[PDB]
Length: 224
RNA sequence: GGCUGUCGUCAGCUCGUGUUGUGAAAUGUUGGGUUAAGUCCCGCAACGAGCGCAACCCUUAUCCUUUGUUGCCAGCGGUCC
Ligand SMILES: [Mg+2]
Ligand SMILES: [Mg+2]
Ligand SMILES: [Mg+2]
Image (cartoon, rainbow, N blue to C red; front, top):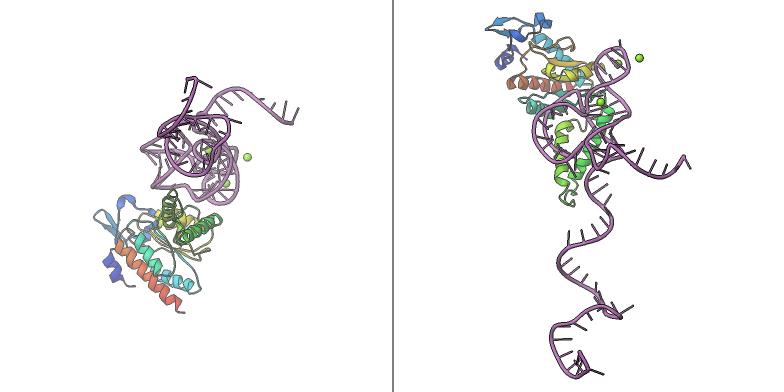
């Protein structure tokens, strides 16, 4: 990827000076109208090694999971993962789903059972007293954990948009030695993650081109 | 030992894994509505489960089907009535 399209998306535009984390001193260019301007000359090579490691680990059948719960980016990341032969999560991250996988897999199994019940021609013999509420439980639970139903294991890498808002997940990432690739703007902590690509994390355009670059990266990785 | 009263038919009482704290412990069980109810919905470092609440049990109030004795007498005939 080149600087032109990411500049078009608005990567330089960031947050004001009242909410800047001093942990990212070299990740800044200057101040322009009471809002920080994120440096772009030092963000493309790091993104290059990030993509290189991503496709290197994807070429080895390395499953990765996509995290994003912003209301302006849930559908975009969901579609990117769907077209990116990987897994995704949209709603609130169930705390400890990694460190307590042996309990979440039971919910996965009961989701499969209820899915079979739904597509089994069975939800009509009920006396209209539980079918509707069971259906409601179905869409709630598929919105919750229906994106990793067939995942059946642990990831090798992990990719997050707007790392700060999903800090919880990153913690469980560091509890198990899973490398993390994430993008942090001017109000995040760059110590808990070893793959930093500074940029905006609020515009739909930003997440779209980031997901497109990730998708192309896994395309070229899988052809090895 | 067994059996019984009481708080009180009050709505509460706990467990597994995870996370937080040096620790006794906490969360889950907090918050906004709502109900007789820890009843339900939304949110949420919690995800699930159990005993409790409710339901399944008995009786009373309406209708239908099966049968008419020692129970019944609308329609007929007779009658010491
Ligand atoms: Mg401890
Ligand atoms: Mg002690
Ligand atoms: Mg407690």
